[PDB]
Image (cartoon, coloured by chain):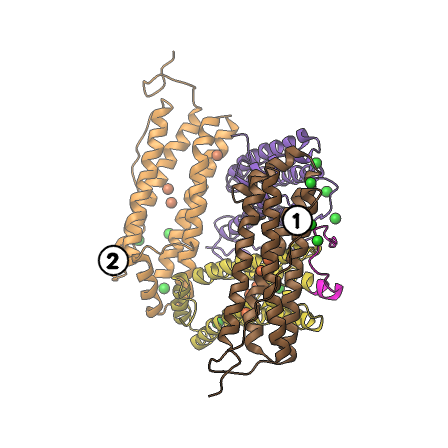
Chain colours: A purple, B brown, C yellow, D orange
Amino acid sequence: VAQGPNGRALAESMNPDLLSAIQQHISIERYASVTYLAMSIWCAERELAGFYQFFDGEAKDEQSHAVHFTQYLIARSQSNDLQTLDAPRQNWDSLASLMATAFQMEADTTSSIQSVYALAERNSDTRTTVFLDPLIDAQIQSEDQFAYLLGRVKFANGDPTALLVIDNELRAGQTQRG
Amino acid sequence: VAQGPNGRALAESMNPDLLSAIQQHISIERYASVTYLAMSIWCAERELAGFYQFFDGEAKDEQSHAVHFTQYLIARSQSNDLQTLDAPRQNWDSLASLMATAFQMEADTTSSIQSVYALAERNSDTRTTVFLDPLIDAQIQSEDQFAYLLGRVKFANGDPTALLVIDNELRAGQTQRG
Amino acid sequence: VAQGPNGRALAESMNPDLLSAIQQHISIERYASVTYLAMSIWCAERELAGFYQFFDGEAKDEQSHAVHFTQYLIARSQSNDLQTLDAPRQNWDSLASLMATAFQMEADTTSSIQSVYALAERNSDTRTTVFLDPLIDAQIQSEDQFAYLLGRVKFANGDPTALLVIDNELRAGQTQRG
Amino acid sequence: VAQGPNGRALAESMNPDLLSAIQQHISIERYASVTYLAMSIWCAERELAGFYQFFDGEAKDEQSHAVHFTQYLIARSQSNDLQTLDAPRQNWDSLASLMATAFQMEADTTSSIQSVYALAERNSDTRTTVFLDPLIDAQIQSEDQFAYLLGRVKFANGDPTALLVIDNELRAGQTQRG
Ligand SMILES: [Cl-]
Ligand SMILES: [Cl-]
Ligand SMILES: [Cl-]
Ligand SMILES: [Cl-]
Ligand SMILES: [Cl-]
Ligand SMILES: [Cl-]
Ligand SMILES: [Cl-]
Ligand SMILES: [Cl-]
Ligand SMILES: [Cl-]
Ligand SMILES: [Cl-]
Ligand SMILES: [Cl-]
Ligand SMILES: [Cl-]
Ligand SMILES: [Fe+3]
Ligand SMILES: [Fe+3]
Ligand SMILES: [Fe+3]
Ligand SMILES: [Fe+3]
Ligand SMILES: [Fe+3]
Ligand SMILES: [Fe+3]
Ligand SMILES: [Fe+3]
Ligand SMILES: [Fe+3]
Ligand SMILES: [Fe+3]
Ligand SMILES: [Fe+3]
């Protein structure tokens, strides 16, 4: 039995470029987390309590995704390399602008997973494509959800009254089309 | 065993300037109470039932704070001196103006506690600083809450529709960021 | 009513040096979080499942502490500034060495809080000292707990049998003297 | 409607090389089953009751996997061909050696599935890749589990005391990192 780079018994070796791509993707999930924390704060500063609660939860969920990836590297007997984390964006001129950045962050997270997926396919790493499949499915749902929240905020067209109504929807847990 | 100014057994004497400051602070709590009663009435007169219910409760809570302080003076064997109570402000041109006065009243209540706290420290009265610590913590929460309500009302920008939505939030007990 | 640096109504201004110190302390809590994540991974790589579960939870708790501080800055109408986060230490020669780093991380977190506390006192910021008091109390308990775990691991004197027994204690939730 | 090789209505023909590969893989699952039975016996002979119970269950689960594959061939209207089954390995010099063989057996089971998967892709058999996807996911978990058990036994470094502790873990159902 061979030993993997992290010292555990090795079921099958992993291409170093694929390993590097997964380590970088963990940083993307961690960066999404701190970005949603920054967004939660921006909303709290403007008394948008439902948006604050929503993004507070999204921050925790993205961190959970990051940990899920670190566990996959452990399972593959590969080394983890937790990286320096950039500071998030923290300033927006409007809730609509913030929600556009949020949607872009979600779509960019999917693009990162897609890049890992394509590298796994080039390397015939079926364990990794199987691992990523349900994460892509979750991303479809999250993109659908963020398009819904962004579109509803844009429909409000900057009217504070409409934004208060949507804020109360989010506080109540009404965060997707259903 | 020595007898304190109120006749009870005396655990430790209290500086008369500190005693006077606590008696004055009790008046500040009582004045906050009648101010919030006046605000509850102003809101009721304009059919803002959620704001009326909110300030009705705040009036009762501030009175409870006043009584809590009178009990501390009893516990320290110090005399209470219930003072003449000024009439509250009763007229405002808008809900936003009323909420600004409410926030100022809350911040001024904290400033009064801080002044007592500093006098207690100058006199090495550790019982009094310990007594005040949780009251300062409550004040942080109340300032956060009043900044939230004031900010939400200001966001409404005088639109009656938005103010009705917020009024219904308060009636439902949705009074802070959560 | 004045507006604070984050735009909310301002109960009382905060010294900019104290604000900077709190923002830096939030980074210390976030760094403790990612350090405990790195430690959880190191333990998982060596099949120390109880230590992995323990540090996984500590990572989540430290993140919660960081968010708790960001909420205090919101409550004080002060700006948050989420900073770049250093990569954690990730390599140790033994569990005893890892636990020494963990204890040091906990003690250093307390030292950071103490530095903020002293600055708040120099500035007569009683809200901040009151806010920090229960966090210092939690730190006493955490230092006691980490001294217990470190001491128990050192008592094992590198014997794998003893380390398996302690690992099973942690998996069962037996993590302090009780 | 066409009839498949097993006589049932045929939704889509299957490449004979892919069919042969699935029939061979069923033998691999059956061989894993009897191998884990042999390991359960070896452990029972040495009073390692927790390891005996663990491998007894693994033997039953691998047989269930084999039957799951036979049901897929039925669903595809393909013939099953149950093959002669080799005798398992039955002798090991130590529990660590046995656990290495167990890990290798698990990794080799995954390699067999991967070989079927690649053949299905070459033949554009999307039903078969979809069928195999959750089985690969289960294999990731089983490889992670067997790496954990092997690593814990190796950490024991042949100390009977440590092996008794781990044996009791397995009897209690504590068989993975959790
Ligand atoms: Cl920014
Ligand atoms: Cl907007
Ligand atoms: Cl951006
Ligand atoms: Cl008046
Ligand atoms: Cl108004
Ligand atoms: Cl006034
Ligand atoms: Cl390192
Ligand atoms: Cl050690
Ligand atoms: Cl260090
Ligand atoms: Cl043999
Ligand atoms: Cl052994
Ligand atoms: Cl063999
Ligand atoms: Fe994510
Ligand atoms: Fe996401
Ligand atoms: Fe009060
Ligand atoms: Fe008050
Ligand atoms: Fe902390
Ligand atoms: Fe800590
Ligand atoms: Fe306290
Ligand atoms: Fe199997
Ligand atoms: Fe298996
Ligand atoms: Fe799938």
Residue at screen point 53% across, 83% down: B12
Residue type at numbered disc 2 = Ala
Front-lying residue, C173 or B173: B173
- Subunit of mark 1? B
Mark 1 lies within 8 Å of ligand 4 (Cβ measured): yes
Q: Residue D156 falls in which quadrant of the image? A: bottom left
**Magenta residues, dominant SS class:** loop
Res C133 quadrant in image: bottom right
Residue C83 point in image, percent of width and height = 70, 56
Q: Residue at x 33, y 70 (%)?
A: D161
Q: Are marks 1 and 2 in contact (CB under 8 Å)?
A: no
Q: Which residues are magenta?
A: C1-21
Q: Which mark is residue A175?
A: none
> In the picture provided, is B160 more to the left or to the right than C99?
right
| Residue type highlighted by circle 1 | Gln
Please say whether residue C134 is one of the residues in the magenta stretch: no
- Looking at the image, which is closer to me, D121 or C127? C127
Q: In this figure, which residue is indicated by the disc labeled 2? A: D44
On the rendering, which quadrant does ligand 19 occupy? bottom right
Write down the residue under mark 1. B90
The stretch drawn in magenta includes residue C8: yes
Closest to the observer: C63 or D106? C63
